[PDB]
Amino acid sequence: KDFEAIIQAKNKELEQTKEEKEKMQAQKEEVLSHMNDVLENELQCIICSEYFIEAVTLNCAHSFCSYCINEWMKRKIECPICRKDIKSKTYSLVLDNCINKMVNNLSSEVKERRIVLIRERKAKRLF
Amino acid sequence: LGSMEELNRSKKDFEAIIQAKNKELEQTKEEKEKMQAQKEEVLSHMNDVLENELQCIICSEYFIEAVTLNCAHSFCSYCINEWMKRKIECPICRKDIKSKTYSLVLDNCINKMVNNLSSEVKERRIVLIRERKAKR
Amino acid sequence: KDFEAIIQAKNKELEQTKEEKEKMQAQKEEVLSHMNDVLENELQCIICSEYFIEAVTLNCAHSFCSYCINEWMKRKIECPICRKDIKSKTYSLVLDNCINKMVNNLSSEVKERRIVLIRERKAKRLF
Amino acid sequence: LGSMEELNRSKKDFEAIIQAKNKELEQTKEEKEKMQAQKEEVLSHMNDVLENELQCIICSEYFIEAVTLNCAHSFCSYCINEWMKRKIECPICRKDIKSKTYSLVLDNCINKMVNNLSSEVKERRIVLIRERKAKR
Ligand SMILES: C[C@H](CCC(=O)N(CCCNC(=O)[C@H](O)[C@@H](O)[C@H](O)[C@H](O)CO)CCCNC(=O)[C@H](O)[C@@H](O)[C@H](O)[C@H](O)CO)[C@H]1CC[C@H]2[C@@H]3CC[C@@H]4C[C@H](O)CC[C@]4(C)[C@H]3C[C@H](O)[C@]12C
Ligand SMILES: C[C@H](CCC(=O)N(CCCNC(=O)[C@H](O)[C@@H](O)[C@H](O)[C@H](O)CO)CCCNC(=O)[C@H](O)[C@@H](O)[C@H](O)[C@H](O)CO)[C@H]1CC[C@H]2[C@@H]3CC[C@@H]4C[C@H](O)CC[C@]4(C)[C@H]3C[C@H](O)[C@]12C
Ligand SMILES: [Cl-]
Ligand SMILES: [Cl-]
Ligand SMILES: [Zn+2]
Ligand SMILES: [Zn+2]
Ligand SMILES: [Zn+2]
Ligand SMILES: [Zn+2]
Ligand SMILES: [Zn+2]
Ligand SMILES: [Zn+2]
Ligand SMILES: [Zn+2]
Ligand SMILES: [Zn+2]
């Protein structure tokens, strides 16, 4: 019987399974990285570092919490991020709804913190 | 030790290597399937959000150049611009349109999430963007 | 008795009264001219030539009837008057209320015409 | 015709001139008072509108650089700009302020009407404009 051939076939099987695993790991890491980038870098208010609460979008296309941008605007009428003079504000149902859905998949600590801020800021639109 | 015993130990030694390799193989498969599940769960989350929160109600596609109206509703720039050739009112709430604002956060979130989905999904979006920018 | 002096005093009295009258006439004409200028040149919509109905003011500071500017905007997104790209609209309670008060002092023909257009355009804000 | 008769006709001729002049004088006064009434009626109309429709609720003056908010309420530019240093909400309806738009029609109407009022009223406005533009 070819004992050497049995070992070589088991070794290739193992090598194949390892590369499959390493690929799946890189794919997993890439997706999570991208998800976290969205959470941390797109959906967090630059003024308060929280996920937007009652998101408002300015004429310059940047978004902020309603509470945050109003406090800012009492002192300065330039977008915090791009410094263009602020000419319009609008609330964004889609951003609020997207954020609620995303946050719903996070830890109950994160979820409860968000609830506390919402009530603390009297953020009515998030019923 | 005599051939029957020497044969038996050589068999045990060979089998121990095979079994060590099968244990590694099995464990590697389990780690692979775990990361596959972890990946799929995040992909499921992205699909849920994209399909149920980030689709334009007019075209049913993920927003392409998302714009937000004064009434807080959002649409593709193309779709609302076509709508406004006939009615200056929100397709959803029918309030008079007073302002239209591009939303970078919506666009970046969509672009970043879609980048993780299949080639078929990514390509459709690229085609749709090209179609909408094309001259007519 | 000085008959010549009686005639001269009556003549001066008359001359004084005539100049007073001519001054009052010029003042009267000036005020009316200004009132009509406001009515005809400030409070009339350039698109429909009616006193504004449901006045809307654009980012460029020009005002139009709501109905008129919406029809315009289906075809062009430039202010009719200054041709700047339209970026915002807002209704104006003060303009509507001012116009109602002014029109209230005009003929019942003008008042009834305005009522007809309001209902014809379904101009809700003017209850 | 004899002196009594010649005297009498000379008296009648003199009196006829005086009476013709008094008739003219009386008629001229009536035309003057009529135009005075016509003028005052238009001035009353302007005052009614200015006082009851074109005053800023914050300062009680006729609007100086009128601005209109998204909620359709108007204020002086100076007054709303000062208010917004403390609250980003309409002083009248308390809605969140989303836009602030200068209104040429309001400004031109005020300027044109005020130009017909007393020197005292016109001067106060000029002073107030100067005060608000002054550095501080
Ligand atoms: C969209 C319409 C076809 C479908 C249709 O024929 N109806 C609408 C059905 C709804 N579905 C969609 O629109 C789809 O999402 C598409 O946009 C789809 O995404 C495309 O494949 C992508 O490009 C029905 C016709 C009536 N339309 C209405 O939308 C209803 O009246 C309704 O909304 C009510 O007004 C409202 O709900 C109140 O109850 C077609 C038919 C005629 C087209 C206009 C021709 C003249 C002008 C040419 C200019 O160069 C562009 C502007 C345009 C005004 C045109 C716009 C648009 O192109 C029209 C309306
Ligand atoms: C207006 C206030 C004095 C009168 C006052 O002391 N109160 C308001 C009374 C209302 N009357 C008026 O404002 C008048 O119309 C004046 O504006 C008048 O026209 C001037 O003579 C013309 O220049 C009471 C204090 C509380 N203020 C309120 O307005 C109430 O809280 C009320 O509105 C409620 O918030 C609301 O109704 C909710 O119920 C004074 C007192 C302290 C001042 C701030 C100091 C610090 C900052 C300096 C900056 O360089 C400019 C910004 C500023 C935030 C200042 C703004 C303003 O200058 C203030 C508020
Ligand atoms: Cl700027
Ligand atoms: Cl422009
Ligand atoms: Zn914030
Ligand atoms: Zn910005
Ligand atoms: Zn769309
Ligand atoms: Zn809407
Ligand atoms: Zn009009
Ligand atoms: Zn204009
Ligand atoms: Zn004021
Ligand atoms: Zn208001």
Image (cartoon, coloured by chain):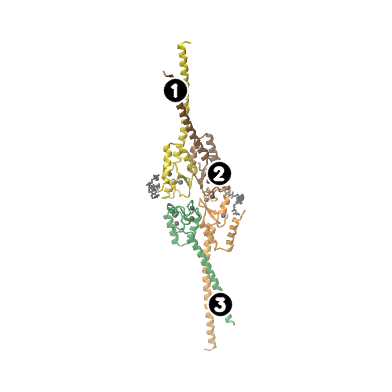
Chain colours: A brown, B yellow, C green, D orange
| Of residues D99 and B27, the one drawn nearer to the viewer in this rendering | B27
Q: Position of residue D36 (x, y in %)?
A: 53, 67
Marks 1 & 3 on one chain: no
Q: Is residue B92 above or below residue D134?
A: above
Q: Is residue C127 visible?
A: no
- Whether ligand 5 has any atom under 8 Å from the Cβ at mark 2 is answered as yes
Q: Position of residue C85 (x, y in %)?
A: 47, 52
> What residue sits 48% from the left and 39% below the top?
B112
Identify the amino acid type marked 1: Gln
The residue where tag 1 is placed is A8
Q: Is residue D107 visible?
A: yes
Disc nearest the viewer among 3 and 2: 2
Q: Position of residue B92 (x, y in %)?
A: 44, 45
Q: Residues within 10 Å of mark 1 (few under 14, many from 20)?
A: few
State which image quarter holds ligand 5: top right
Identify the amino acid type marked 3: Asn
How far is the residue under mark 1 from the one under mark 3? 138 Å
- Between disc 1 and disc 2, whose residue precedes? 1
Label 1 marks a residue whose chain is: A
Q: Which mark is residue C11?
A: 3
Identify the amino acid type marked 2: Cys
> What residue sits 53% from the left and 65% below the top?
D40
Q: Which mark is residue A68?
A: 2
